[PDB]
Amino acid sequence: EGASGFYVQADAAHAKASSSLGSAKGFSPRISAGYRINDLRFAVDYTRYKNYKAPSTDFKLYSIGASAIYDFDTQSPVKPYLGARLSLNRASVDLGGSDSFSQTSIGLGVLTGVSYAVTPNVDLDAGYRYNYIGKVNTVKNVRSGELSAGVRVKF
Image (cartoon, rainbow, N blue to C red; front, side):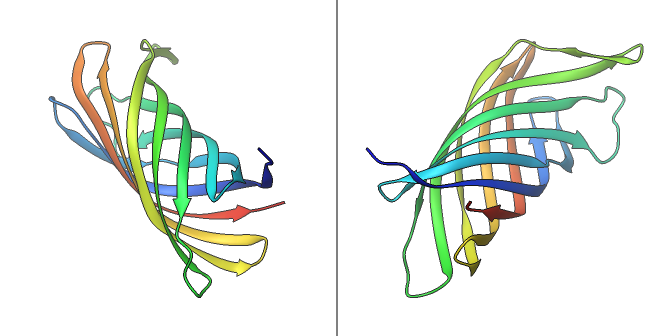
């Protein structure tokens, strides 16, 4: 109805990916862009997961997501939040030097966390995301948990 407080955010994340085959640990840098309407934040992000240590079959995970988030007001620069995320997900496996990708899978996740306002234009953000990514070319019940820390600049 009237958009405002456009912004960009970068996060670093410790992640755990799981499936019916097992689980693995790694890192999940994220970049997003967004804005506020009403008291809601909307954002698009690109995330890419890598293993710390490569299993016999190494892989990467990629998503592009759309998030809707509610920020709780307190009497303070500390602001809890709660949200939901829809995503398009792919996996990668290296094959003679080159990545080869899986089909695309729709994912559904929850996000929560806390922001701190450093100044009226800059926030720090400590978060948890959980994503149900489902079935990625053969492998079942793919899911991830991510703990993150980032910076948001509302230009």
